[PDB]
Every structure is written in C-alpha cells, then in structure tokens.
Amino acid sequence: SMSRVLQAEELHEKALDPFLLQAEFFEIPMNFVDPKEYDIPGLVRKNRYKTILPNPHSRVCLTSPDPDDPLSSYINANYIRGYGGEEKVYIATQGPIVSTVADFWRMVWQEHTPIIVMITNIEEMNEKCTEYWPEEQVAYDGVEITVQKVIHTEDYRLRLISLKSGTEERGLKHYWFTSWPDQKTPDRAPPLLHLVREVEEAAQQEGPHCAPIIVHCSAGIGRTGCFIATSICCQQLRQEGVVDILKTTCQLRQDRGGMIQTCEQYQFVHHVMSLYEKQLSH
Image (tube, rainbow, N blue to C red; front, side, top):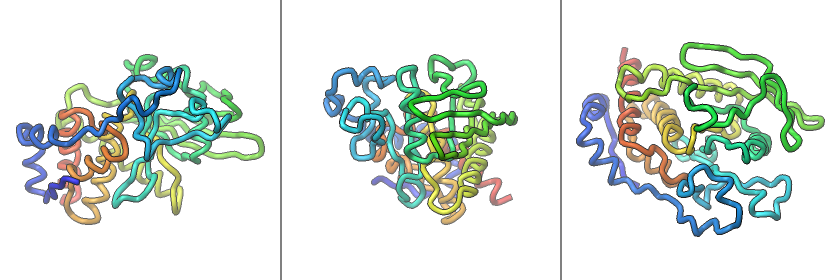
C-alpha cells in the first residue's frame, strides 16, 4: 500500500536515521481489529491481549473438535503472506496460554505445520509463553507430541519433534530463539539474520508448497512481524537487489493487525537488512 524501495546505500543510511524511521513507521496504520468482531462469550479467555485480535479475513479457524462451536474453533492466529504475496507462508500467532496449548497443537496438526519459530527469551517463560512442549512426550486433543532431540546452538535451540495421531506420523522442527535483544542495536542483528536463514533453509527442505510456518512470541505481532518481515525482505534482496520494508510491513499489517509493533522493532529490521546487504556484497 505504501512503498519505499531501498537500494543498498539508502538502506544502510536509512537504518541509522531514527527520525525518518519513526516518521515513516508511525504513518503505517496498525489495522487492528475492532473487538466487537468477536462478540462471543468466553472468547477473551483465548486471547492474551484483549485488543490484539486476528483479522477475520486471514484468521486461522480450527475445525476440530466441534467446528460448529465458534469458541472451539477460535485461535488467535492469522495466515501471513510471504514474499511476492504467496499465500499462507506463515501463521503468526500468540504464545499459547494454558487454556490454548491444546488449540495451538490442533492448529499445528490441522495446518501440517513443519516449522515453529518461537522468539521468546528464557526470562519471559510462563509470562510471555506457556512451555507448550513436553520434556519427552505429551498428548493434546488427540495428537501425541514427542521431542526426539534437542540441538543447542549459540542463537537458538532446535527441537526435532514427532507428532502422531492415529496412523499418521509427521515431523516438526521447533526453533526457539533466545537472543532477542532488549536494545535493538546493530550488534544484535547477526543472530536474527542467522535464524532467518536457517529457518528459510529448513523451509526449502520441505519441498514444494511448504505448509505454513508458525511464528510467535507473546502477542504474535511484534517480534513475529520482525522475523517475518526480515525473512520476506531477505528474499526480496536476493531476488530484486532492493528491499521495501515499508511495503512488506504494510502487507504484514493487512494480514494481521500490528505486525512490527514498535519503531525500535522497525529499525531493527533495517539494521538486519543492512547487515545482510553488506554480507551479500562481501
């Protein structure tokens, strides 16, 4: 909707101009959802944040266990277009709360999601995210989740997981990124860029028409928007030799209100893309 195509030089300078960045960022409408849209008793129990709600056109609806029950079928999640508008590359969702852990896994099963990206720091567990995976094994509304392996790396912990419901077995990779910075300075960009590249490469290993990749921290918009915007713009940089973070943010906002919630987040994406362009140029 809005657009600012950045070539390399402007990109490096734009990332370092916070006055222009906030001018640009706060012109982007949030596109938040009127809470009246989900006037369903008990629904507020499924939301972490009463005013961060899934836009209805892109909302993920659960069909299990009662599709005729608007509360049973509700999850605070949206399909998110990827690079070039490709449909349903991601699902942005809130960190599960105790009342929605089973819903979250129902989503993962329903959507054939191969990859979860969790952008939540150690400190913020059981406040910004319920530990929704087992030590080894656990079962939710019919799907058995088995953590087969944990790979620790500097920037993230990767769990290899198996999901079994009845006769069907599927794999899942759970990337738990733990280096989200408090200060979104350029020295903190490399781990995010690394994660984006590792995830986009895991995604390619799933083959054609990869099922949606679930991305979350707490509300499903801020860090989640940063990760998705960075992933999209990395493809844009590789394919087009430019980045349009403003247009990408608008595309994200159209899918889910509030994606990239803070100007510090918005500037961080620019720091990450500036770093990546330098890497690519060598």
